[PDB]
Each structure stands twice: as structure tokens, then as C-alpha cells.
Amino acid sequence: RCTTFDDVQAPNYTQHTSSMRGVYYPDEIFRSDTLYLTQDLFLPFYSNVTGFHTINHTFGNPVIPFKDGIYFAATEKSNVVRGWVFGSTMNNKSQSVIIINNSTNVVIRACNFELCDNPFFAVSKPMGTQTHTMIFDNAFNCTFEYISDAFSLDVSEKSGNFKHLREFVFKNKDGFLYVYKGYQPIDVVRDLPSGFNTLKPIFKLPLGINITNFRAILTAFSIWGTSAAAYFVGYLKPTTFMLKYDENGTITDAVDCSQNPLAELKCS
Amino acid sequence: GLTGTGVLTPSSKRFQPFQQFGRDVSDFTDSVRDPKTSEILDISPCSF
Amino acid sequence: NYNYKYRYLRHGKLRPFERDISNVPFSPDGKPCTPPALNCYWPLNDYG
């Protein structure tokens, strides 16, 4: 069932600053004590940040395109917006990939999928039983299925500090699927703190479809529910970067070239 | 996949769980997390 | 071997390591059709 509700309006397209967030471990390889150069589809520093300021007045999941490198951020409160189904036509006639949980364990399938206009997690307000998580409806001419580890993973409706921070990068490479993660406990009102953190290679799935467009998945509080918050979106752009690696073997200072003529001479 | 020639000796470092290689100035791997749980350096220059 | 097929119709060129099954009622500018209505075919083709 496209169990699709009534409070989705068109937004004001609110944009913010992309100071230094979005750095990851570029390889499996140690370095130390240099400025190392390479080029990648990265988020440009200081640039726009797509802030999606979903509150009780506005639920936010439109059509969401990939468009050549992406970045996900959410100052979570017990991990509300889990679920990534990536594909082309977002229907039965897209073999897509469903990337969801049984609240402990990552369950992923890639197949023709009954991709409804709204399937979700019908999560309650005080306890959190996903009443209507029926997303594995149909699967024919399938391709793939994957199950990770059961790990500690909370759902329920909360507020307070922005203690959880899902910082995700989902990167493609010739079908291969690169999953980065880095935890960073923060608390600003919901204005964006600046900063920088290593993102770290959780996963690969080698899938390989027409990876065009998608949506998010949230937990609809069976009146749906989001609270006084947002979530931040970026794209990647293929430019060349210089990193300053310490003797402690850590990402410490990432500096682009093409942002700034200053940054160009720095990497020069 | 790494043959080579030199001297080995244990690390003094801050290694990572996914990690294997170190490539000191370039393409050298510098170190091995041994495939049965050790983490040592590399000094391929024996003496010469 | 009428059993097995390939596809020979697409908008544009391929990208490495990608699979799409979708037997589109293919047409040069969209047109979700009932083939073989004219300028509307399918990409699939047998082996013989």
C-alpha cells in the first residue's frame, strides 16, 4: 500500500554553509607526516548545505535524486530516518535496493520491489512497534540479498540533545557500493556547527543498477511524526585535495585546491 | 600478495582495524599487520 | 534456442558493471507504448 499521508508541502529550499564536514578515509592504507594529494568527488568546503527542516508542520520525503556523489547528515535522536532504497524508477518496474533494519540487523535486498508511494515504519510514540513495515512485498526477477550483523540500534520518538549524529556517505564505484560512517555527538539549537570528522568504510555492496533516484525512509508514528529538527544534504564534485596526516595516523586537516586560490597555492 | 626483501621488527604505532599497509613516502606498505595477528614495521633496507 | 535473449535498445551508452532487466516499450523520446505500435518496440531479442 502506498500508505501516503496528507501533510507533505513544497519547501522554501533552505540552504546553509558546508564549512568542513564530509572527510573520509580515502584508502585502506596508513600514512603519516606529509601533505598527500589526490582527487575525488568531494563535498566542496564552505558551500551550500541543503537543510530540510521537517517539523510536525511538514513531512519531508520527495523524490530524491542521486546526481553524482552525495552526502547525508542527521543530528539524530535515536535514529529516526533509517532506510535507503536506491534505484531508477521507484516502482515495481525498478529493480531497486532496499537497505533497512529489523532494528538490530541490516537487511538489504536488490530485486523488483513493490516500491510504493509511501511504505514506511509504522512506529508508535511510547514503545515503537513498526506496525506496517511491509516493504518486502514483491520480489521477482531478483538480483541480490544481504544481511549484516545485529547491532544496537534504537528507533523511538525522543528529543533533547543532538547526541546521535548519522554522518553518512553513500559512494558508487562501478556498481560497488561504499558505505562510510562517523559518530560525532553535538548540541546546537539546530544551526549547523562547523567541524570535520573522518568517515569510515562500513560496507560495500557491489550491486550495479541504474542508480538514479530514490527517497528516504522514515518512521511514521502510528498523525505521523517528525520533531523540531532538520536533515542536511549535499552533493559531491570531482576536485583535488591535500591532506595533512599526523604522526598519530589520523585525518587532521583536509584542504581542497579548487575552493580558493589560497587553497590552490596551499596544495601547489 | 607481498613478497619482498629486508628486515622485520614490531611496530610502535596506532594501527586501525581495517588496515594493513603504511606506504611511508610512497607505495611501500611500511608495515604489516601479519595475517595471524601481529602488527610490525618494515625495513626493507637491510644494509647495503 | 528461442529461450534466451539479450537487449539491443537503450537511451545512450552503458556504464561499467550495471544490470537492468526492464523490457521498456522502447521509443526514442519516451512513449510508454503497446508495441509494436509504430516507433515502439522492445529491446529484447532471442538467440536462434
Image (tube, rainbow, N blue to C red):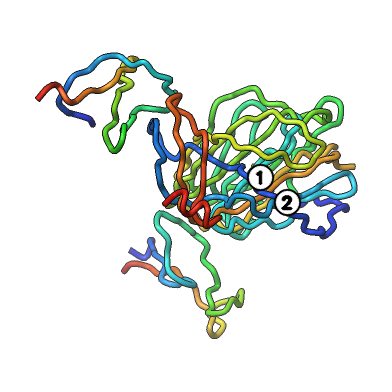
Q: Amino acid at mark 1?
A: Asp
Q: Nearer the viewer, residue A65 or B31?
A: B31
Say whether mark 1 and mark 2 are on the same chain.
Answer: yes
Q: Say if residue B15 shows up in the picture.
A: yes
Q: Amino acid at mark 2?
A: His
For label 1, the crowd category at 10 Å Cα-Cα, with few meaning under 14, some 14 to 19 and many 20 or more, is few
At which x and y percent is residue A87?
A: 58, 54
At which x and y percent is residue A229?
A: 81, 41
Q: Is residue A24 left or right of residue A155?
A: left
Q: Nearer the viewer, residue C11 or C37?
A: C11
> Which quarter of the figure has residue A168?
top right
Label 2 or label 1, whichever lies nearer to me, is: 2
Residue at 55% from the left image edge and 36% from the top image edge: A199
Q: Is residue A116 left or right of residue A175?
A: right
Q: Is residue A65 left or right of residue B29?
A: right
Residue position marked by numbered label 2 in the rendering: A16
**Res. A137 mark:** 1
Residue at 84% from the left image edge and 54% from the top image edge: A8
Q: Nearer the viewer, residue A46 or A201?
A: A46
Residue furthest out toward the bottom:
C38
